[PDB]
Length: 295
Ligand SMILES: O=c1ccn([C@@H]2O[C@H](COP(=O)(O)OP(=O)(O)O[C@H]3O[C@H](CO)[C@@H](O)[C@H](O)[C@H]3O)[C@@H](O)[C@H]2O)c(=O)[nH]1
Ligand SMILES: Nc1ncnc2c1ncn2[C@@H]1O[C@H](CO)[C@@H](O)[C@@H]1O
Ligand SMILES: [Mg+2]
Image (tube, rainbow, N blue to C red; front, side):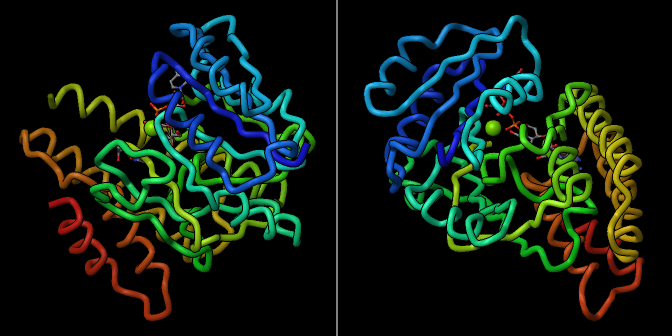
């Protein structure tokens, strides 16, 4: 009724158990909450789901074919009855404040809250987020249009007004950055009021020919998405120009068989945020920082 948790899942029955248990330890009245698990035509997870359902109002949906996270999430958005929807990937965990920390902002007039993200390089549980080897923390406020440049959060961090009621769904033609496209669909396409909640955190758990072709899917979907959704300030429209620069440097390294920094994208976001801010750096300066971020 109040909140629908949507968990797309695929061949990770055991991570899905951790995510569900992190819903069960929510500091929240469970009579107001439903959970929708969507098996994207992988190994069955009935016994995993029938276990948690002894406490949560849980629904298991079985896809007719492997549809990608877009098609699986959409299946959840279609039946989610909550005024509000909270996405949770099957390999991530909520903190117990995930809803008590976001719902007051939504009831107050927000349409879309994202919380802080801890990039967890060790597996954790919901009540033990702050016992993990935290590699990076994504905590960028919404004051600069960073989200217009490229994505800086993840669906496990998002609680938002019923997208089925807005008629806003995931694009099934995108297997990567389908979330970036969806966030802009809500914020621009449907004028959702985006608000950052920095007092709540999730734990997000995260070959050359292999790598070059992989990042190329990302750049090409990033161009697609940029073209579909123009930036809502001129500075952000200018700072998009440094993304193909960052890609070119990534490709250069990959071709020389040199590895990039572990979280070079997340170091890149910090450079792009800087470039969007009060004293504006010259492009040669950003370029030098994109270097360090990637080295
Ligand atoms: O065919 C698939 C693959 C995955 N999933 C589920 O989708 C979620 C995300 O999959 P995962 O492999 O964990 O994604 P990440 O690599 O962590 O992130 C991807 O999905 C993110 C949102 O989770 C986007 O931010 C990024 O573009 C993209 O890299 C999880 O619930 C998966 O179980 C499906 O339902 N179907
Ligand atoms: N604009 C973009 N948005 C999201 N991801 C992007 C991206 N450009 C590349 N990537 C690639 O996807 C992974 C990011 O964590 C990593 O594989 C790599 O950084
Ligand atoms: Mg993941």
